[PDB]
Image: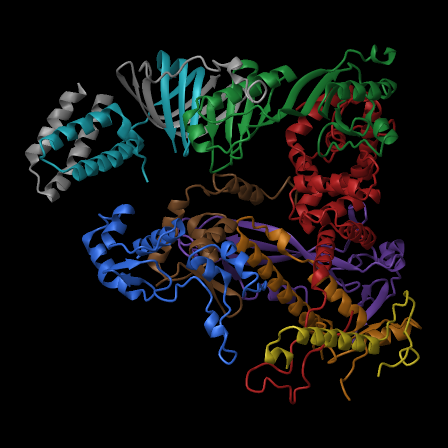
Amino acid sequence: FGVLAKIVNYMKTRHQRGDTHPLTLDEILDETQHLDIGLKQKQWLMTEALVNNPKIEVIDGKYAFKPKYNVRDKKALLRLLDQHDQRGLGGILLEDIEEALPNSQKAVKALGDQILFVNR
Amino acid sequence: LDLAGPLLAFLFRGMFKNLLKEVRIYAQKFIDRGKDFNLELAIKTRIISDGLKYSLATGNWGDQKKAHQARAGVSQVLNRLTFASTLSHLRRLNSPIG
Amino acid sequence: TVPKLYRSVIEDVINDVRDIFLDDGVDEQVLMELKTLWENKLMGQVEEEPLNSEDDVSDEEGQELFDTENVVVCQYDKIHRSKNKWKFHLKDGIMNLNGRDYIFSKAIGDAEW
Amino acid sequence: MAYQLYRNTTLGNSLQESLDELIQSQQITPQLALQVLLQFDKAINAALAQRVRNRVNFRGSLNTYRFCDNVWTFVLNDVEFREVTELIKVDKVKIVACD
Amino acid sequence: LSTMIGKGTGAASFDEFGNSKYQNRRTMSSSDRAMMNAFKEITTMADRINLPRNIVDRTNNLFKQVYEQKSLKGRANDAIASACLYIACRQEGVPRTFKEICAVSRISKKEIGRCFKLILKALETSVDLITTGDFMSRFCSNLCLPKQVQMAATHIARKAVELDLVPGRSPISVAAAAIYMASQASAEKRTQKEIGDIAGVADVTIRQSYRLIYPRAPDLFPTDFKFDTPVDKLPQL
Amino acid sequence: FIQMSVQRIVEDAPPIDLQAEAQHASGEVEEPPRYLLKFEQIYLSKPTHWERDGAPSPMMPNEARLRNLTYSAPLYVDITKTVIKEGEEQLQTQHQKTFIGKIPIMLRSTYCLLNGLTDRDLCELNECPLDPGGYFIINGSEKVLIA
Amino acid sequence: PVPPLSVRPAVVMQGSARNQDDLTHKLADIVKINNQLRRNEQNGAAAHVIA
Amino acid sequence: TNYKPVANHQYNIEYERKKKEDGKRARADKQHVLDMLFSAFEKHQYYNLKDLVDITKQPVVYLKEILKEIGVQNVKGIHKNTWELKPE
Amino acid sequence: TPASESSGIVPQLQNIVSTVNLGCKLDLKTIALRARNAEYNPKRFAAVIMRIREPRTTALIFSSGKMVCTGAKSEEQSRLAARKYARVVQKLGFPAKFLDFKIQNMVGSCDVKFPIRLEGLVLTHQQFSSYEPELFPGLIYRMIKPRIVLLIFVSGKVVLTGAKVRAEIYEAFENIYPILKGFRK
């Protein structure tokens, strides 16, 4: 179990470094020096641990970063918000910063476009 | 007839148990923290000292807060009017009643 | 006396790894070869940091390179100091002085720096 | 848990050198050698506790000292080891201590 | 503030299904509920050494001043309470030793003392200096020593400090050695160990102080006293 | 009541023991410490008074009335501490003799000071030889219990 | 209606206005818990505790 | 009514214990502490923070600082809280 | 001054406390490990302890890069010691600086050589003096002239502390000396 949380921490660090490109389990285990964690642990990790996580992005025959397998569009769904009978999604700033890029660069344009900040 | 002894035995009994619980509460809080027990520090001497003393003074029987209304004149200031009132008052006995 | 102790140790170690050698499937001749080998082996700058005007805050690079130190390996019970006065309460020790072999169950010392 | 420090000993090193020969000859495994070292460690610790009974008192000059990870390391000069029935003077000694 | 409620008449008083007759009472003064708990400790302690309520009332009063100033909020109430008991006892002219207050308190002698100096500065006030006379009574009485011995002891103590025979010494140790001298000259001889056990001082502290006063022993006694043993026959320790 | 009942009550059957919690989140080894408290013989000293000085002395009922004292005596008990833990130790036991409180004395009973004295000592002490006694003195008031 | 002081005679009995009558003590709970109930309700409240 | 020492004898024992090695903690080496959290996650999905400081021997403010970084929390009933390394 | 030629004996400096900041973050573990004549106990304390032989001083260096140097019997020796410490640290390959070197405390002592009456001194200065034999065998005087603390003993010995510059010691001592002479047994 604890090696899977070390893999998720490395993949989270890969997005924080600037990247969401898919890798094989090998390339992850090599960089993290877990290649020799034992063939039984590598097999379990491949055929149960990266299968039991529903948030993993499966792309190009490989696994990618990490909390969202969909809707990582890194911008607000303005189109849904246009519809006053169904417009609905404010969320937490931490998910949006986690998603892709820092808030501030997007926000300068957004402070005069769509965004409102509430200290909730 | 409940004289001085059966009446006192009651009052002191309730107080010593009250004191036994107080040493238990004290020893339990310490032992949660750990290692420094002192037996002499635990005893709240006032439980006995003041408890018998208050009841003998007011007349109010039993411990306070809850039950007390049961008995009121179990104690009195001794009537020193003649020699006979003293002697008679020391030997007076009462039935509880409406 | 103490060569005997090392002998005692020879007996205890060899006996306690016999079974382990056995568990690996290794032959007792290797263990005997081990023992024989072992027995044979046994015998700004102007104000911010003008510090270079204070160089040599040392008398020597080191002393352990000289190997002039007979070695001592031991556990400690108490270490104490009072200024230049140090106090040592040592225990369960193995000494080797000028090639000679020594031991102690307890050692107590004093030293000045 | 007993301390690995006695593995540093000349005796302990003489053992390791004997083991490395057996490893060079590949008659045993490195893992097995490590296991012999653990047994020797326990054995020599047990032997010190049970057998050794002598005591020595000493005085000298302290030259240098270290303390890290609960391990004291000294180097004393002009040291004088005194036993109840013996005397040993030495120019310099290295002392490593852990407990 | 206000009132409280309890019991139930034994009639309706719903827990309806569960077992909670009508309603439980409620706390009201939690913010200061530790001032009342300080007072509870002050009274308990006080009774362990059996002071009159008047001392206890001043102690209670000193605390309320220190607490409201909040200047010492960082230390345990039991440390501040123990200091109040010590100050109050000294100001009332019946000093207690720190060793005595430590015995009844759960606070160590060091912390009561440190708090004590800080409170004196905190209340911007001072106290009288202790003298030997202030303890002579309690000690001689607890050892069942006759009134006459106590009187001599007081005199010996008093005369000795007047003669400056003990330049740097606690008044307690000097008192203790005086008492010992008096008692060893009395029929009711008591061991150094007993006195030391009562005064708190080490028996070696008595040994030194007795050794220092012994060379002038003849001159220190009061003229009214009648020896049981000649002073040329008073033992040394 | 003294010769029997106050003894009977502490010689009851509630010896208390206390076992603090241990091996929280982890432990293994061997001891969640355990303490037991026992009570023995009870002692009652003749009725004493302590001055603000701290020095105790005998009280006499006439004094107790004038100065409004309470005529009571101090009570002591033998207590035991008994460390029979889970294994490491069992015998470490210690006896104490401790002041627990002050009980009022009934006047001229065997625990009063008046109980042995003749006509001469009582006239001397300032107490009337003809006074029946048998009643408590509480804060300077004579308080008699009623059957 | 809060009785005026003439109904709540400030029992005095020595003290220093120590006699803040007992009806006043009942009134001090009523304002206290009501002050508390209004303030409780001003914020968020579980349905049972307000009950 | 007992001789009054400088402090309780046992209090001094308590002082001596406090005065033996244990006191300050080993905040250094985050990775080994990270490993210990992983090891906690090897036995069970959630634990009491009281247990977490006991098993780690680290200061609370720091153990929190780490638990904010790599995990989340979940409370139950009356402020009874447990923390989890985001099981997935 | 005439008033300082009677008690002129003039007090002797025994201890100085100074600080200096190296202005850089440091790895105490590595430092402690590499350095000779040094001690570091992380499980019982948070800093490394260092000692030089010359003028038996000792310095304490913190992870922040701040350090404190004590033991000098003179400001020169304090400047000398601080520099010697900052040197060996430089020699550790770390960007050691001499920046913010400052005296924090100075201790002085002297002997007036006469028996002193203490009950009077505490009487006359109850707003300042405090003498409690039950706590410490020596009267503590808290001066507010050059806000200084003094320890006065029956022997005649006197210690003074709380100063950062020598003038404050002479001033505190010139001030208190007449009183002490006037309470001479």
Q: Which chain is green?
A: I
In front here: D79 or I20? I20
The residue at 71%/68% (across/down) is E28
Whether residue I176 is situated above or below residue H13 in the rendered picture: above
Q: Which chain is brown?
A: H
- Chain D visual colour: cyan
Quadrant assignment, res I151: top right
- Chain E visual colour: red
Left or right of C15? Residue B26 is right
Q: Which chain is yellow?
A: G
Q: Percent from the top left, x then y, of residue C98?
A: 29, 13
- Chain B visual colour: orange
Whether residue G36 is situated above or below residue F95 in the rendered picture: below
The residue at 23%/26% (across/down) is D13
- Chain A visual colour: blue
In front here: B24 or H61? H61
Left or right of E97? Residue C10 is left
Quadrant assignment, res C45: top right
Q: Percent from the top left, x then y, of residue C22?
A: 10, 42
Q: Quadrant of the N terminus of chain E?
A: bottom right
Q: Is residue H47 visible?
A: yes
Q: Quadrant of the C terminus of chain E?
A: top right
Whether residue H84 is situated above or below residue I157 in the rendered picture: below
The residue at 63%/52% (across/down) is B41
Instruction: Count the labels in the image.
Output: 0
In front here: F49 or H5? H5
